[PDB]
Structures are given as C-alpha cells and as structure tokens.
Image (spheres, grey):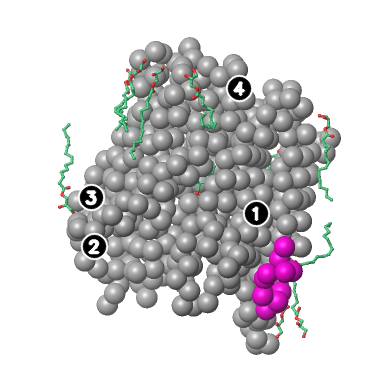
Amino acid sequence: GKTFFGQPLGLSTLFMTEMWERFSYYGMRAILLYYMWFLISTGDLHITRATAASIMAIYASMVYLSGTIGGFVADRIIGARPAVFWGGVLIMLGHIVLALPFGASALFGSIILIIIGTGFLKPNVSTLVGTLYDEHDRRRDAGFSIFVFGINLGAFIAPLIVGAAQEAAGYHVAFSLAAIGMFIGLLVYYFGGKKTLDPHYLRPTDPLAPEEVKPLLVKVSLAVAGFIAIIVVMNLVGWNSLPAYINLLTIVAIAIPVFYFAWMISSTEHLRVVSYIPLFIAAVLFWAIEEQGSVVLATFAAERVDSSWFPVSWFQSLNPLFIMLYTPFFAWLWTAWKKNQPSSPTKFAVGLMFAGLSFLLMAIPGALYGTSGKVSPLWLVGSWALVILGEMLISPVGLSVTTKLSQMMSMWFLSSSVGSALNAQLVTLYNAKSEVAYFSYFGLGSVVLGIVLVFLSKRIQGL
Ligand SMILES: CCCCCCC/C=C/CCCCCC(=O)OC[C@@H](O)CO
Ligand SMILES: CCCCCCC/C=C\CCCCCC(=O)OC[C@H](O)CO
Ligand SMILES: CCCCCCC/C=C\CCCCCC(=O)OC[C@H](O)CO
Ligand SMILES: CCCCCCC/C=C\CCCCCC(=O)OC[C@H](O)CO
Ligand SMILES: CCCCCCC/C=C\CCCCCC(=O)OC[C@H](O)CO
Ligand SMILES: CCCCCCC/C=C\CCCCCC(=O)OC[C@H](O)CO
Ligand SMILES: CCCCCCC/C=C\CCCCCC(=O)OC[C@H](O)CO
Ligand SMILES: CCCCCCC/C=C\CCCCCC(=O)OC[C@H](O)CO
Ligand SMILES: CCCCCCC/C=C\CCCCCC(=O)OC[C@H](O)CO
Ligand SMILES: CCCCCCC/C=C\CCCCCC(=O)OC[C@H](O)CO
Ligand SMILES: CCCCCCC/C=C\CCCCCC(=O)OC[C@H](O)CO
Ligand SMILES: CCCCCCC/C=C\CCCCCC(=O)OC[C@H](O)CO
Ligand code: NA
C-alpha cells in the first residue's frame, strides 16, 4: 500500500537524513575555500591560496578515508543507528565551530569533527537503507537509487542556499545554515527512525567477542603511536609546516591501498587482483579530476568567470545537478543496451576519457581569450557536463566490478580518497599563470590513460 516511491516507508527517513547531511557537507564545501581566501586576505590565516586549495583536497580525502572505517565501528562497537546519530551530532558541531566568532583557529577543530562525524554517518545510513529490505527483496536496487537521489538533491540545493546566505549575511551565518541543515537531518532521523528502523541496529550486529577487544586495542594503539612518532620526527628535522603535514596525510592516504595491493598480490585468481590495478588507477584519476571541481574549478569560477550577478559558489550545484539529469537516461541506456553492452573496464576507460575532456575543454577559454580576462559560465557548465558523464560510467559499476574480482571492497571507496590525496598535491600547481598548461596536461594525460585502458580492456574482461 503506502510506500515511498515503491519502497518501505523507512526510506523516507534515511533519504531526508542523508539529504540534509549532504546539504550540510556540500554547503560547507561550496564556501570553505573562499572562506580561507577571506581569512588569508585579512591576514588572519597565514597560508597561500595554493595551500588553501591543498587543504580542501586533503580534507575530502580524509572524509572519504574516515568513511571506510565508520562501518566497522558501528557494526562491531556502537551500532549503526547510534553511529548515524552521533556522527550527525559531530558533523553539526563541526559546522557550529565555523559559525562561532572565530577565524582561522577554528578551521582544524571543524575539519576534525566533520571528518569523524561523516566517517560515522556516511557508511551507516547506507547500511540502514539495506536493513529496510529482506534478502530476496527485488526493490533493493530501486531503493538505493532513490537514496542516491536524496544525496544528490542535498548536494544540489546546498550551494544555492548556503552560498546565497554567505553573500547576504557572511560566512558565519552561512556555516550556521550548514549546521542547521544537519540539525534538521538529526531531527528527522531521530524521531523518524524510532518508528521504522529495526531496533536490532541500536546495537552492533557483530559485537566484538571478548578475545577480540585487546587485539583491536593493540592495533589502534600501534597505529596512533606510529603516526604520532612520525609527527615527532617530522618536527625534529624541521618538516613541520602545514604543507608538510598535508604531504604526510597524502602519503598515508596513498600508502593504504598500495599496501593492500602488495598484500593481496603477494599473498590463482591472483591474476584478477592484478587486473584491478588499472581499474583502480583509472578510478583514482577520475576521482581526482571530479573532486577538483570544488577546488580548481571553484577557483576558476571565482577568478576567471563573469559571475557578477550570482554567487560563484553556486557552480558547485552543477555536479549533483548533472548526476540527477543524466541518471534516468543512463538507467534507460543500460537496460535498453541489450546487445554488445560495454564491459566495466571499457566504462572506466571511457569514463576517464570524459573526465579528461572536461579538463581539456577548460584549457580552451584561456588559450583562446587569454587568462587576464573573464569568460562565460558556460565553460564550467560544459566542464561539469563532461566529467559527470564520466561519473555515470564509472560510479554505478565501481563497487560492482571491484566485487566480481572485504579489503579490496573498501579500496573502491578508497579510490576517491586516493584521488583527493593526489589532488592535495596537484591543485597547488594551479594558478592564473599555469591555467592552460594545468588543464591541458592533466586533461590530455587522463584521455591518454583512458586510451591505454581501452587497449587493456579485453585482458581485464576475461579475468
Ligand atoms: C547524453 C549525451 C551527453 C551530452 C552532454 C555533454 C555536453 C557537453 C558540452 C561541452 C560543450 C560546452 C562548451 C560550451 C561553451 O564553452 O560556450 C561558451 C561560449 O558559448 C560563451 O557564450
Ligand atoms: C580516522 C581516519 C581518517 C583520518 C583522520 C586524520 C585527519 C587529521 C587531520 C585532518 C587534516 C586537515 C588538514 C587541513 C588543516 O590542517 O587546516 C587547518 C589550518 O591549517 C588552520 O591553520
Ligand atoms: C553534545 C550535544 C548533543 C546532544 C545529543 C542529544 C542527546 C540526547 C539523547 C541521546 C540520543 C541517543 C540516540 C542514539 C540513536 O541511536 O538514535 C537513533 C534513533 O533511535 C533512530 O534510529
Ligand atoms: C541545538 C543545536 C543548535 C543547531 C543550530 C546551530 C546554528 C544556530 C545558531 C547560529 C546562528 C548565529 C551564528 C552566525 C552569527 O552569529 O554571525 C556572526 C556575525 O554575522 C559575524 O560575522
Ligand atoms: C579509529 C577507529 C578504529 C576503530 C576504533 C576502535 C576503538 C578502540 C579500541 C577498541 C575498543 C572497543 C570497545 C570494546 C567494547 O566496548 O565491547 C567489548 C566486547 O563487546 C565485550 O566482549
Ligand atoms: C585517544 C586514542 C588512544 C588510542 C587507544 C584508544 C583506547 C580507548 C578505549 C579503550 C577501551 C577499553 C576496552 C575495554 C572495554 O571497554 O570493554 C569493557 C567490556 O565491554 C565490559 O564487559
Ligand atoms: C579523536 C580526536 C582526533 C584528533 C585529530 C587527529 C589528527 C590530528 C592531526 C593530524 C595532522 C594535521 C595537522 C594540521 C595542522 O594544524 O598543522 C599546522 C601547523 O600549524 C603547522 O604550522
Ligand atoms: C598504511 C601505512 C601508512 C604508512 C605511512 C608512512 C609515512 C612515513 C613517513 C612520511 C613522511 C612525512 C612527510 C613529510 C614531508 O613530506 O615533508 C614535506 C616538506 O618536505 C617539508 O616542508
Ligand atoms: C535554470 C537552470 C536549471 C537550474 C540550474 C541550477 C543552478 C546551478 C548552477 C548555475 C550557476 C552557473 C550557471 C550560470 C549560467 O549558466 O549562465 C549562462 C549565461 O550565459 C551567463 O552569461
Ligand atoms: C546533445 C548535444 C551534445 C553535444 C556535446 C558535444 C560538444 C562538442 C564540442 C564542444 C565545443 C568545445 C567548446 C566550444 C568552443 O570551443 O567554442 C568557443 C566559444 O563558442 C566561443 O564563443
Ligand atoms: C566532445 C566535446 C569535446 C570537448 C573538449 C575538446 C577539447 C579538445 C582539445 C582542447 C585542448 C586545448 C589546448 C589549448 C592549449 O594548450 O594551447 C595553449 C595556448 O598556447 C595557450 O597557452
Ligand atoms: C599524434 C600522433 C600520436 C597519436 C596517437 C593516436 C593513437 C591513440 C590510440 C589508438 C587507439 C586505437 C583503438 C584500438 C583499441 O584500442 O583496441 C581496443 C582493444 O582491442 C580492446 O581491449
Ligand atoms: Na558573483
């Protein structure tokens, strides 16, 4: 009878929970770079714009990385439903910290809170969506598709609302709106959740057995002690600038999948794991380019686009806008394409090519008009139109192609973390002087690697 778009009613709760969480997150993302520019311009924040850009990327990287851990903590320690709640509380506090009358000094506290908060919430709202369905329920795919629509919806309206708020009432109010967004999500989640969510998920579904507590404790302790020792050594030898710490985080984010690889490849469907390397690298490079929209394209939008009549942060709405527009088309395409459907390796290859084209496109206005002037918003619209076209190919089959080849599964989600970590290095190269070369180089490079993957496509599809 009564459903939410054909799904169990409980989906409406999780849909809105995540919509408002994504609202809070992408509302923040859409103005945080500009906020750091502002803090720099007033002499409050003593970093370069390049470093500010690097912060944005490594921020995203750590958020993605944190998300690969929150599932474990919920499933084994605190439960999925408390994970989402307290995750949301931390996210909200993270935005509240930026709304307070502080400047640069509040940035780190905010970043940590949201990293931890999102890590708790993001994987576990997804988990709770699954719990709405029996094993044999054919609606599961549809329900997640609707769930993802809620994600994109929140990502879409946030830059519009928060960005406008920022320009009208300043950054603190804008960040307060992101906080309020999360609060709304928490209200709907908490009271909505009590009614439709299985009480089972108030507790861990796979709680630590007695003999598991100490080994986990030792693991975490060694990791923290090791990380801290590195920071001590870094400060002793004078590698203690912010870019230095960002490099450390870059190294950590990249080393984690490198080590899982070295593990699996060393430890015979070995051949299959080897086949994932080009797919994973393709995913990483795609996510790198896609995640640069909130950094390099946001920079381009503010410095190089004639946007005198609307908030420049609004460009951040194009990414989720195009996902939502493309989605029913690609949904149709993959069912209608019965004969000769492309392989997932081919989708990755073509997906990366489109990402490459999105940057190659952005090289044109600077090459044609020079970089001193300002250009139409349509250049960015076209760029996002292209990279999202790439996303429609890689994103829906990403988890899929990885699975058909638990550690390796997290690596799919890690590819975006690695992509953002790569960005933390790359985006420091972007400026007005390097603009055309930046877009050309990384655009062409991605296309070439898309072509390389096309050549490799047949091998991979057999394994
Ligand atoms: C399902 C079909 C996929 C097709 C969607 C991909 C759309 C790609 C568009 C890229 C071209 C955008 C460049 C437009 C542009 O820069 O014009 C600026 C100039 O006209 C200033 O007025
Ligand atoms: C639980 C795994 C997730 C990884 C957690 C580690 C995250 C640690 C630090 C976040 C790094 C953010 C760097 C940006 C940053 O420091 O900006 C602060 C400004 O420099 C303030 O002066
Ligand atoms: C630090 C200020 C934040 C204060 C948070 C509110 C504290 C009041 C009650 C604690 C709420 C604990 C509920 C945890 C939880 O699992 O919520 C899930 C709901 O049952 C819906 O699934
Ligand atoms: C129960 C948790 C509360 C969740 C709501 C958090 C946000 C609520 C109020 C914050 C709004 C006021 C902060 C913005 C502000 O004061 O601006 C300061 C001046 O405009 C200086 O720029
Ligand atoms: C950075 C996140 C990585 C995972 C964090 C784990 C938290 C640190 C150490 C593990 C402590 C877990 C508490 C054990 C617990 O509460 O349950 C005990 C068992 O359920 C009873 O046998
Ligand atoms: C600040 C990070 C430090 C890194 C190590 C984190 C250690 C944090 C908490 C250790 C929790 C102690 C484990 C024992 C425990 O909680 O189990 C109790 C049982 O559930 C009672 O039967
Ligand atoms: C459960 C609490 C988690 C505590 C945070 C864990 C990660 C802490 C630090 C990661 C390293 C990032 C340091 C960034 C930073 O502020 O350094 C900038 C310095 O001012 C260098 O001039
Ligand atoms: C899953 C295992 C994780 C492995 C982490 C190993 C990280 C060990 C050392 C990282 C070195 C720290 C980087 C510091 C650095 O690059 O300095 C930056 C500049 O040269 C100083 O301005
Ligand atoms: C009416 C379009 C459907 C709703 C779009 C949502 C708004 C999200 C981003 C729009 C901000 C950047 C677009 C600006 C634009 O396209 O203007 C083109 C004109 O030629 C300006 O010279
Ligand atoms: C459903 C139609 C889909 C068409 C999408 C394919 C787009 C093909 C080429 C993109 C054009 C490259 C940028 C446009 C360009 O260079 O012209 C320069 C500006 O028009 C100068 O005013
Ligand atoms: C299907 C739509 C295709 C849209 C993207 C197609 C763009 C293809 C090639 C654009 C590459 C632009 C090169 C610009 C360039 O590097 O010239 C340098 C000039 O000397 C200015 O520094
Ligand atoms: C400017 C001179 C160099 C220009 C290089 C252009 C050649 C680049 C790519 C050739 C792509 C040919 C497509 C054939 C191909 O990839 O086969 C697909 C595989 O058989 C499927 O795995
Ligand atoms: Na503007």
- Disc 3 Cβ-to-ligand 12 distance below 8 Å: yes
- Disc 4 Cβ-to-ligand 13 distance below 8 Å: yes
Q: Amino acid at mark 1?
A: Met
Mark 2 = which residue?
Answer: 461
Q: Real-space Cα distance between discs 1 and 4?
A: 28 Å
- Front tag of 4 and 2: 4
Q: Which disc, if any, is residue 201?
A: none
Of the residues under marks 4 and 3, which one precedes in the sequence?
4
Mark 1 = which residue?
Answer: 16
Is residue 232 in view from this perspective?
A: no
Q: Residue at x 66, y 56 (%)?
A: 17
Q: Residue at x 76, y 51 (%)?
A: 183
Q: Real-space Cα distance between discs 4 and 3?
A: 41 Å
Disc 3 to disc 1: CB gap under 8 Å: no
Mark 1 surroundings: few (<14), some (14-19) or many (≥20) residues within 10 A: many
Q: Amino acid at mark 4?
A: Phe
Q: Amino acid at mark 3?
A: Val
Q: Which disc, if any, is residue 310?
A: 4
Q: Quadrant of residue 12?
A: bottom right
Which range is magenta?
192-204
Horizontal arrangement in the rendering, residue 294 relative to residue 280 (left or right): right
Horizontal arrangement in the rendering, residue 385 relative to residue 55 (left or right): left
| Quadrant location of the C terminus in the rendered image | bottom left
Of the residues under marks 1 and 4, which one precedes in the sequence?
1
- Disc 1 Cβ-to-ligand 3 distance below 8 Å: no
Ligand 6 quadrant in view: bottom right
Mark 3 = which residue?
Answer: 454
